[PDB]
Amino acid sequence: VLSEGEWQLVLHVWAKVEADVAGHGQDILIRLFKSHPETLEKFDRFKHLKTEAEMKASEDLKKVGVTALTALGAILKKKGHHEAELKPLAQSHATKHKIPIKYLEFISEAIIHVLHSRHPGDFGADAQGAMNKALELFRKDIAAKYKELGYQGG
Ligand code: HEM
Image (cartoon, rainbow, N blue to C red; front, side, top):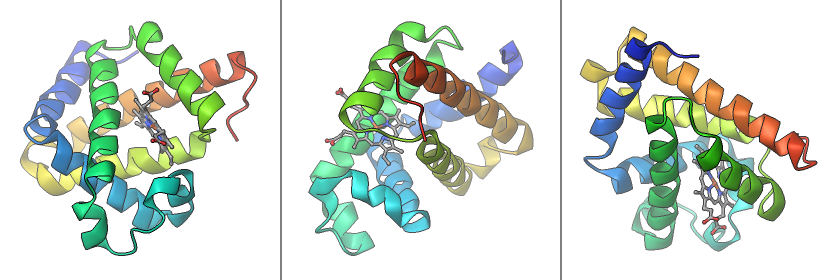
């Protein structure tokens, strides 16, 4: 799917994320919630967080962000050979929480935005394209695992 060069650009910027998984996770979630507020409804433990400062102060939100970016990091490092990592995540998202593919599109946008905000010198056009392809492949494979479980992802 992705070229070896595209994967290298993906994993190069991901190494920058790993310098501060918590801070990236916070900014991505807060960007997702501000750009698409309906996504905040999937997090009942976050309903009382009304301001950006309250979200940044919530260790719970921070930990949830770290858990997400950790799983995505492990998937990206498989360079497309991620069935074993993607199936449990698809099941969690399709049976417990029911997350539509469109919401995975929303957070992908927030991921790209935060990465370019923090690392423009390591996230120009070729790298953005590479990361977009990797996230597209993630969403496409999650969608197929969704259907396999009987959840159509809408
Ligand atoms: C790249 C995108 C995402 C990744 C990698 C991801 C990953 C994860 C992981 C690893 C868990 C923990 C599951 C477990 O231990 O069984 C989780 C939980 C969850 N995810 Fe996602 N997720 C993503 C996107 C989203 C989006 C966009 C939403 C909602 C808008 C969402 C909602 C949830 C919820 C509600 C939970 C359960 C956490 C809790 O309620 O305490 N996720 N996610």
